[PDB]
Image (cartoon, coloured by chain):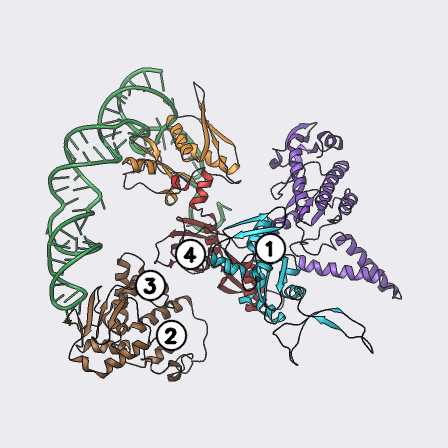
Chain colours: A cyan, B purple, C orange, D brown, E red, F green
Amino acid sequence: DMLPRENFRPGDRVRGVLYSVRPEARGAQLFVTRSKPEMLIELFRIEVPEIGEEVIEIKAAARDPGSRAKIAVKTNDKRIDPVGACVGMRGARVQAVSTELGGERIDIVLWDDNPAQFVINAMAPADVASIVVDEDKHTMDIAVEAGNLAQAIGRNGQNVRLASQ
Amino acid sequence: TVSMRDMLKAGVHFGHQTRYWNPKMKPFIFGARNKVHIINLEKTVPMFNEALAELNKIASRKGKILFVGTKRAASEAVKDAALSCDQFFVNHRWLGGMLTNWKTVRQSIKRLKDLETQSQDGTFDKLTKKEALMRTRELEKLENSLGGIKDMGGLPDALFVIDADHEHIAIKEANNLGIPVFAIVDTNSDPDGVDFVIPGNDDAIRAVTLYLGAVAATVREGRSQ
Amino acid sequence: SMQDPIADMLTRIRNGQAANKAAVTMPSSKLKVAIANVLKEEGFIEDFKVEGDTKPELELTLKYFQGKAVVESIQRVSRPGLRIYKRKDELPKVMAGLGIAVVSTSKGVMTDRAARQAGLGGEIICYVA
Amino acid sequence: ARYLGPKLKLSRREGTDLFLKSGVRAIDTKCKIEQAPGQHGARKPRLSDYGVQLREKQKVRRIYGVLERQFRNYYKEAARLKGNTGENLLALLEGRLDNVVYRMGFGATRAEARQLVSHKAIMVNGRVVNIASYQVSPNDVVSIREKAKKQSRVKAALELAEQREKPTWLEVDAGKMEGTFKRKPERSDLSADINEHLIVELYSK
Amino acid sequence: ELQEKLIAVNRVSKTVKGGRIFSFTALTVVGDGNGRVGFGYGKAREVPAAIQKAMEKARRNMINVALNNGTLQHPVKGVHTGSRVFMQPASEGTGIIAGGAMRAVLEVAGVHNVLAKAYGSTNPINVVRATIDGLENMNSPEMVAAKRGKSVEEIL
RNA sequence: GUAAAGCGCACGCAGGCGGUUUGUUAAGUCAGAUGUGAAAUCCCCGGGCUCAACCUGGGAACUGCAUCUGAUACUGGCAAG
């Protein structure tokens, strides 16, 4: 349930969503898993003041935990910077929120009315010349230059997986 | 979807007296019978249809609709409409800054919820009689005000309104935030704040009901889709 | 008394634009007609229509793009009180070229750019933006 | 006609390293480069709009070692000339003979270069030029004369330069001790930290 | 990414039975160095709080401005209350030639090159508003083309 | 309108401005040319004093005035409506 590389030590606090109490010998004990996207989602909910008041809505939160993450959010018709409000001063929300995950590489991303734009805005940070998504079998096909492709793919397809997810 | 004949039967075509009109409603007016303004059903119907379509579309993307009507004649009906399509509503007085000042009103909602829980799920009873009474009163107050919107969570993605002049505060709020507005707008009302104006009789009960029902149906359809 | 007809026409147009009037009618004159034509060419109005024999009425049909009016500004420059004549080098550029300046030249009334192209200046009637 | 005082003080005042000392020893070791000069150094309240501009102007002036009237004249010239004003000004500044020499690497500091120029060490197209403000043109070869070629300081300067990045707009020969001013530098070739625009604004009061 | 400049801060008083209650008004303006600008006017008993409020205000209700490269698209007048403002597009290198509150708004907006005079009143709050208005009204060539039913080459 | 500022109200000479159509004129207006608008100064590209100031070659400019030849939409004159 923990990170692969991030090793905890005593004196370090950890916040997580607990999900099970399995009855062991001589009574049960609490168990958590501080690696889900629920953890970063609630962390940004406790972080952003516009998240509670419905000025902006969190459309999708996608995380490869500890490694790399991309969440797409939009403003609920206020002409408001969702990345600027969910970022704080100089990243001072999300770079603090990444400290909740233990070093997450998180990207707040834009989203628009039509789903096509959302998918095109979920390919950041990478430009997209054209996108041919299949209307039948959910198989959006994005096409651009090699330079953007590398950034649109990432290490083990993180960006692709994130966007796809 | 909704026919012209039905509308006529309801009393949509009737408007307010000529001295109380707004000249911004001059396009939607047809004529004046017995010194009372008649709304043009030829211009109304298509607009209404369009509005309905829009609503349906909104529903389809899991949009939150808010039904506003604080006339007190059609308070019962609007609530019913809301509940049929399991959507939210404000059938009693609109709290000034319900949407613009959501974050404060979110606290109120929470409080109300807590009160409800105390009333129902706790089953504790054993409370000082005056205090208990006070609590009950508070609960009643909350229910009346924020009963429909308690499960709304955030802000709505569209706003259906039964009277534009009466609910101008709501409309204004929706404009400031940019929420789409779907107002029923009689001849006395102002259509400028409204996005999807519906020229029709706000006052008559049957007409109001008709307006509600179709909308509800469309929302349901959207949900189904 | 009525002293400047072109000016009056311009004013009328402006008022129409303000008040969201579809079409604006006025008593016709040749110069006025020419101006209207020019405007149409430059795309600030939809169409103009003169009608009548004894006392004909010019009717312009105003244009509205995305709610708001097309004729953002429209000022007389020459006026009976104080006439303005420009030489082809001194001809203005309204809104840094985005607007037009109606200028009456020896070869008829035309936009400023047109006049420049021709190689001639004249009486500057109005700026339109 | 020259600033003869403490050089590092100026740098401190500015905030940045102005390159007023050779660069053998790092500036942080020689002085408290972060702390401003004088009794009230540690205190640092945010400056005014005018003040920032003034500071910027000073920085540039300090860097090249140009007094105010001269600077003003240069600015005026730039304004007169076609193209971007600040850029033009920068180019003009660069064009100074002493500056060019420094760039080449015959002077450790700009001051040193200036001194050399003064003392009839440098030639421009085989003619001894003594003026530090002399605007060196494109394709104008500039060299150390045979008398001053034996000096140990010159070689040291060259060495220092070699450690320092080479400018693209020149071409210098260490053995021959002659450099060709190939072209007037582009803005991209110069340092990005200099806000020329502020300077321009200051004089456009 | 957003840059934010506190233009002015002013102490304002309210007389009460006891004496004078003082407070502070902060006028700020924020922009992304492109078209987007927004001013905010915040008020509080202490300065920093007021400033913060102003900033918050600014960050919502922004406005877009069509910018031809670093400068404006054509000379534009903007008025609001006493402050009437003229601003004129200018060649690369010239810098923001403008005074006070007006300058700040321009800078955030990401205009680099302007010639701008503030006639009339120079009351910061009004003048910034005026500037904003001017920016807002200013139409682009493309926009004008769209309006008029023409191509961009027809307009030049 | 309330900040300084609408004659107390009219008639009315001089003056200013003048609905609409056609014709004509070509005064205003515009175009081109010619003559002139001293040199220096200013500005542009150059050259010479080591650089600069300074000196200096050529240009541009001197927004005007006069005359000649056109243009005639607009303003004016004259003639008819």
Which comes sooner in the sequence, label 3 or label 2?
2
Query: Mark 1 against mark 4, which lies toward the viewer?
Result: 1
Chain letter of the residue beneath label 4 in the structure image: E
Discs 3 and 1 lie in a common subunit: no
Q: Which residue is mark 4?
A: E111
What is the quadrant of the N terminus of chain A in the image? bottom right
Cα distance in 3D space between marks 1 and 4: 27 Å
Q: Is residue D182 above or below residue D30?
A: above
Q: Position of residue D86 (x, y in %)?
A: 32, 62
Q: Which residue is mark 2?
A: D14
Q: Which residue is mark 3?
A: D187
Cα distance in 3D space between marks 3 and 1: 40 Å
Q: Nearer the viewer, residue E52 or A66?
A: A66
Which amino acid, by three-letter code, is at mark 2?
Glu
Question: Does C4 sit left or right of B58 as displayed?
Answer: left
Q: Is residue D137 above or below residue B56?
A: below
Q: Which residue is mark 1?
A: A75
What is the quadrant of the C terminus of chain A in the image? bottom right
Report crowding for label 4: few under 14, some 14 to 19, many 20 or more residues within 10 A (C-alpha): many
